[PDB]
Each structure stands twice: as C-alpha cells, then as structure tokens.
Length: 341
Ligand code: NI
Image (cartoon, rainbow, N blue to C red; front, side, top):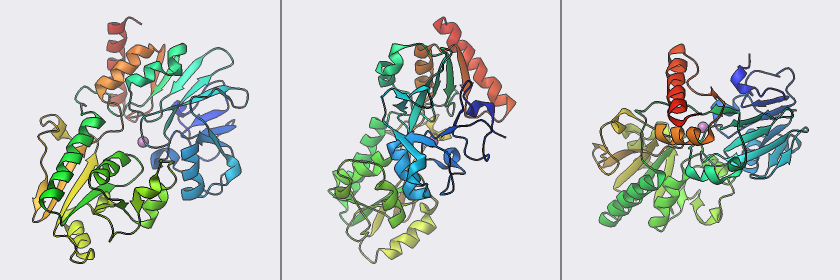
C-alpha cells in the first residue's frame, strides 16, 4: 500500500508511486526521473496520465514503451495548470530529465517535492525565491555529517588529468568507465573530449543516450567499439576477471586499461581527499573509484533547507527504520534552532 510520503494532500496526485497498482483517487502519477526505484512498475500497459519532463518522457516511450498519449511532458520553469492545480517542474541537478515539483494547492498551501536532488545555490535564484513553501518532501540520502564529498567540477578535473596523462604516456591504453543507469555522463564525455575521441558503448546504452537531448550527441558517441578509445561497460563488469575478459575481445589493439568506477560516498571519503586517490592493480588493469555524487552532501542539504525555512519536512529516503527517522529529526531540529524558523 502506497506510503503517505508518496501522496500529495488536497489533490489526486502521487509522486514516484508506480509499484502498488492503481491508487484510489489518484488522477495523475508524477515521475521525478528515470531511475528504477522510482519508476518500478511502469510499462506499455499504463493507461493513466504520467506527468514528467520531456527527457523523462523520451525514456518512457523508447525504453519502457509507454504510449505517447499518456506521456504528458511539461517544460521546466513554466507555470502550468494540471487538473486545475498550478504546478512547476524545476531542474533537480540529479540525472538527465530529473526534476523537483512545486505544487500550488487551492487552499493556499505550497509544497516542494525534491525528488532526488543535489542542492545548489542556483536553486536560491529560481522561482522558489518568489514565495513561501510550507511543506518540503526531501531527498535525505546523505543526511548525516560524515557524508562529505567533493564538487563535480573537482572530480571532472582529476578524471580529465588522470586519463589524458596515461594515454599520452602510453598511446595504446584504453580508457573504460563503469555505468548502470543514467547519470554521471559528464565523466565519460569530459574524458573523451580531452582525448579527441567518441565514446563507444553497447547498442542498448547508445539507445538510452540518444533519448537525452544532449546537444551535438551524434558527434560524441558511437556503437563502433573498434573506432573508439573511451569505452563504457556495465558496472558489474568493472573488475579484474571481467576487464581481462573484455581486454581479450578488443583483439590486440590495446595493452593497458585505465578504468573509472564513479561511485557515491564510500568510507574512504572520511580519510582520503580526491587529489590523493589511488587504484587497485592486478597486472596491466587499473581500476579507479571516484566519488562523483548526484545527491546533496550534508552541508549542501543543510544550506538549502535553512534558506527555504520550510514549516514542515517529510523525508523520502532512509525512512524504513525508526533509528534513521529519529536521527534525521534531530538534524532538522538543530537546523531550525540555528536559523530561527
Ligand atoms: Ni536517483
């Protein structure tokens, strides 16, 4: 049964709640972004409206095969009426096509649902700057002060450096990048750009990328593996046995892989900086982990909430145990007492 933090009061609206069957009274099912925990349940056989971004729509039509009529894409940053309720979609700074949703209730209540987000100061000069938000449904993935990690522009620096080094030292080395969902495209696009290459990938991953409205995408990517020296691979595959396997397939065209596993937080963030990173090494294969996050750090989250001064906060992540719920409330109370709301 749909949990209360997936419903919007005073509406027929639900958010990311596609895995319960029909939801009694739900006229509309919102989807914040194309990640399988949030979309779990959608298919070709859905015959209720789905509101989402244009990009999320393309993924719905082409990857899940939902029928065009039931996909209502909406522009971002545009005041839109939906069953006689004003709503706005705002960029979530998560993956491609990921949005937050502003709901303007008839009664005067304003609600913000963040979806998955990486909070940023540019969100403080958006349409949110113009009015008061009473309820906040918040991505709490990293709501604990241990969770620090670098900026995305810092990570893209390291990456561009490491790869452009090794390839200039050894011009017969391959760059590999791990992946298992949309997100983090900047990692491989930036490396390929510094190397003068296209990124090569499976057909299914090519298909996914062709849905994302990336400008000039036809010049950046290929299904011809042979022609490319930045390859993508399933994240499951990014290990020694699997990289050996893959290094066989390229047929004596490269003599060294240099891989990147973009990850979120891991416990080695607590002790080691990004400039002082190293890889595991079993022969000529070298696997880097790099903490490129598309979720708010604790400090980023804290700042966004303290600016927003919401009257109430409803977590959407780590809500499954009383211990986590309890820890989170304590942080929300501190933030409130510091900031005076
Ligand atoms: Ni996500």
